[PDB]
Amino acid sequence: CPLMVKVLDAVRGRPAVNVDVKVFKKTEEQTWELFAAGKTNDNGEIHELTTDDKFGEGLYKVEFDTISYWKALGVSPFHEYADVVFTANDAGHRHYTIAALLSPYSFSTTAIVSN
Amino acid sequence: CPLMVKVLDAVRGRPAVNVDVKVFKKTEEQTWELFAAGKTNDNGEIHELTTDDKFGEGLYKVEFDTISYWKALGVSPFHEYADVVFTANDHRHYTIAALLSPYSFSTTAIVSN
Amino acid sequence: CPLMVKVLDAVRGRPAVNVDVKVFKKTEEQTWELFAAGKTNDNGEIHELTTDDKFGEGLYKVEFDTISYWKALGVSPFHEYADVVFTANDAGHRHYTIAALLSPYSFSTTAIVSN
Amino acid sequence: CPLMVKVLDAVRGRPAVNVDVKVFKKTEEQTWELFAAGKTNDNGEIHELTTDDKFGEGLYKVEFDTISYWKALGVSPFHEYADVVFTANDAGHRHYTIAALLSPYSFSTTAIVSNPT
Ligand SMILES: [Zn+2]
Ligand SMILES: [Zn+2]
Ligand SMILES: [Zn+2]
Ligand SMILES: [Zn+2]
Ligand SMILES: [Zn+2]
Image (cartoon, rainbow over all chains, first blue to last red; front, side, top):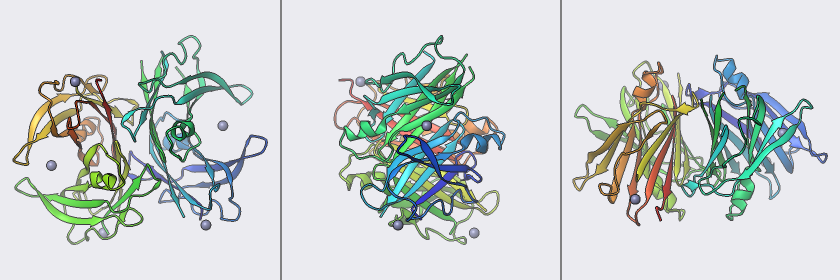
């Protein structure tokens, strides 16, 4: 599984469950085309997402729908969403885990890249 | 000054100097239109990014060009760039703080009156 | 396994391997007594730090030896070490994961608590 | 001013006001002696914490009382407190800002170190 996410909620000290996650890929026309999608499970992870075959070289954007996550818990957050944009698989085959730590007015995102 | 940025480098423990920062604003055509731009100074701040008059209600995107920042220091980082998107319903002042590491990016919003 | 750690290196985008982790527990005499110790593996995890039986109610301190970690990579960091202090198991039995993200001049810590 | 703190609350997007802060310094006897203390103001800063004269070489610990901060806002937090320990002024005279970002189950800290030339 070459693209994973792990989302944690810094307010509750729990994985963030039901965070809608879209992955886009940049096209020759310089637009973002929807590549993959899911919802974080009980562990704040998205199983599947894509495959070594269908992945490939290019520029990807992983978007977490943070505003819906917070609003559903009665919190009024700052950000519309949290993006991670990066070039993938251009210097040999890697696996990417995108970790996101969520607070209402703050976010962090960290990439773990393996071989 | 109603929209500020403060950028820190977590590797050096110094403000991040010369980080290209673009601010966009969402339009009725559903596109991002360039609204403001600058480069962080010696304190990692951009000084007069916009003005109370020009900065109305709407949806804004602050973009930090992190890949250039790092590459120029001989580091090969993870992110192409780092976006902060939010709706200003202001009257309020917004500081976007970013902490930069090669494989991690952290952002906090400070909102005042 | 009721007390886990997960340590990531924000410079390399890799789990932080060989970080010395000591766990202390507060005593009646108001001192810290050494409770457990380990070194992060290839995934930045310590695997069996204590056990449900030995890990009771009280005040604990998890210490990461960050200065040795960085110096060994030729970096001269800011912090001597990074501590996480917390009360555990006082409102019923929980499992605790302490996540740390390391940069030379910055450290971040998050707790994940489950039932 | 050679030692500042700046404390932010990640839940509110506001400076964290009235965070109790203590600074300790390590002694020859291997113990922590209280060196300075304050409460964060409206900007989450404590300013005149110490002075270039009083603040020499050594090992210091800056402690934020996060549990009181949160409890006073009705939040039951995870950490008892948050410590930042570091050696200061051993390679020439510097100024230190310790920035802390607080969430109920998460704590983040960054050091900004400058050379007053
Ligand atoms: Zn593979
Ligand atoms: Zn876009
Ligand atoms: Zn158990
Ligand atoms: Zn101690
Ligand atoms: Zn001085």
